Length: 6
Length: 50
Ligand SMILES: [Zn+2]
Ligand SMILES: [Zn+2]
Image (cartoon, rainbow over all chains, first blue to last red; front, top):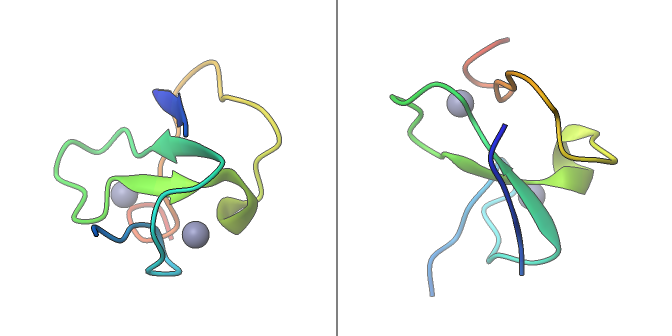
């Protein structure tokens, strides 16, 4: 699954 | 400005995207949906997969 880190 | 997730807060920390391309929320904070790491395969949010 796509993830992001902010 | 935009808010996300089941908690309706701004982006922070690590977030995951629902694999339902029709999801109305799309992005979720890992902690809000019980995740510790990136799912390697499919992942659906609690609203799409109740
Ligand atoms: Zn959240
Ligand atoms: Zn969803």
